[PDB]
Structures are given as C-alpha cells and as structure tokens.
Length: 217
Length: 217
Image 1: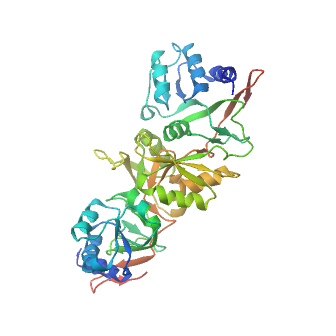
Image 2 (image 1 turned 30 degrees about the vertical axis):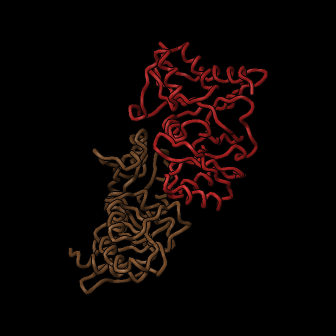
Image 3 (image 1 turned 120 degrees about the vertical axis):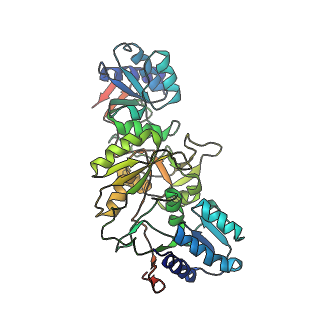
C-alpha cells in the first residue's frame, strides 16, 4: 500500500545473491527496491541480466556490468514480481512490463524469486487479465481462439512491444489448470508469448507484510 | 523434381476453388502454377489472402484483390506446397518461405490443400531441417533446449524474419511423434513459430506423378 512492504520484500531477496555471480533482474517498484539492495554489493557481483530497460539503466548507473542472455549458459536467480500468484506458485505476469523478455530470462534462471505485496496471492489465477503477445496479422484469429477457450480478449490499442507485436489482455477466465491453458494458448498460431508462468513458476516467494516481509518460499 | 509434375499438381487444386470465395494462397514453384490456374477464374473470385510477397505480386498482376488476415474471419481453402509431408499429412514447412505467415494463414483456412511433386513425401519427418523462429535474445537458450530434444540447431546467419526474429534450422531429428514435438517446441520460452504442421496438417494432398495429379482426400 505501502511500498514500505514493497521495500521489505525487495531487500529480503538480497540473501539469495552470491558473491561472483550474474543476477537476473525483473522490474516493478518492488524489484526497484531490490536493485537498491543489489547496488549495496555492486563490488561482489559479476553483473546482471535484465528483462527491463528501466532496471538496466538503473543497474548501469550503479556501475553493475550488463550481460546479454546469449552470453550466459544460465543464471543462478531471477528476481521479479508477479501480477498474480497461486498456492502452487504459478503466476500471471506481463501485465505491466516486457512479457517475452521476462519469460525468457526466467527460463534461463535456475531459481525464480517472486517478490510481491499482499495483493498478488490468489485462489485461482485469472481475475487480472492474462496478457498474450500476438503477431499483428494474427490478432483477430488469436482473439477468436481465446473466446473458444472462454476468455474475453481485449486488444491493448495504441502500443506495440519492442518487436512490434500487439497485446491482447484476456478477461474472465477461471484458470484452473494453468499448465493446460499455457499449453493451449502456446499452441495457437500467431501467439508469441503467454503470460502464464505455470510450467516454470516461482521457486521462492517473499511477500511484504507490515512487520518486514514473509519468506514463504 | 519435375516442373510438369509441379504444374499438374498446382492446376488440379483449382477444382477446389469455390466461386465468390477469397482464396488462401501459399508460395513456391508449385503454387505459381496454381496461381496461373487461378488466373483462369479471376472474374469469379472475390480475392486472395497470401503468405508470400511474390505470390501477392502475381495475384495483383491478374487483378485479384488482396485481403489481409484481419479482414476475413475464415478462409475456405489454403493452397500451398511443403518441404516434407509424412503419410499422416503432417508437414515441415517454412524452410524457404515466411514460416509464421504460412502457419497463421493455414490456421485460418478450413481446408489445407498441399500441392507437391514426388520429392516431398517422406517416411519420417526430420531429414529436411525443421525451421524454428526465435526471439533474438532467446537464441542460445532455445538452441540448448532443441539439443535436449535430440536436434542439431543451426542459426541461419545474416538474415532475420519480417518480425525481426532469428531462425534456427534443426537437423538430425527423427520426428516420430510430430504432434508431441510441436507441443514441446511451442513451449520453449523464446520460440515464436515452429515449422511443424502437425496439429493442423494437410486435408488434401495433390501429388504430381509421371502419370498425372494424384489426389489423396
């Protein structure tokens, strides 16, 4: 409410950061507090991979070396937030940052450290619209397919991804079987990426509470 | 490969063209014969949706109207060649054409008519390298995962797709379960499109033989 719990949470992640390593870094206000923590040890870290322009400019300014995903075989950790997280640590992500870059850095990372306030934990994924990046010539097609799956896809007009793709935000779904829905949407021709992190979810969850953050991994 | 067999196959596809329809049209030498055929019936069709720059030029030469995929809700047919086709009518496609375009136009069309000479049928897919379009920052990652699936991914250097993505051509696979492999690749973060046409394959195969066109419905 309370990006004091956002900050508790973000600094709480610093314990996962090893001397000599390259750190995977997401974005958000709660990650940006983790980047404030991380600069506290700029000297002891080899560098960072980031899924966000804002974070990388911030890491650079702290003098932390930036690596390209194609320069690493893996990352020890990826520290990011989520839009929703369920009891099984499956997430909706990409509602407010670079969906495809987040999914790719999280894929290369050994451990995903999810960093949230009290509002992210849910029963059933899906209240928060599910972002789906779509090749532009396919947008009406993919949208027909999401309707068949019982979603209500809404095109995010006036913007594109760095790649030039469009975003559909899918409302109204009760996402029981996230792994299955991830499968289903990844199968639709014209889909680039789907904001269900269900086959690879959070490994540690750190939730900001009033008394200083809850490491409920 | 014989051009007269390509020619026979492309002309035979013309029987499948309903008057007053918008025709899905692919690319290649075999399809160029089909386009010739379609010329003979042009003032009898509303238009065409094409997956190829060169096919659009040819259809425009004939005065056939061009529609985009977002302008139609379905297509009756899509007429295209293939790199390889198994006896189950599953194809490798995209080796020398616009892979993502073709898979989306085929997803929209009701009926896929695959027009081939005798050199496209194979017992098992995989000799012909499988094209995978990939987000550039994900290239090494996706190649690591393709190697885990048994393949030899080769980066198609010097070039990008319309969308700015890279292509990995994957050698050395014995694609005994095309629907599974499509599912597996479709789920690697960073994959945009896989040249496996397995869940949605060909509905009609017209093969050009030394005798004439042979139709397999």
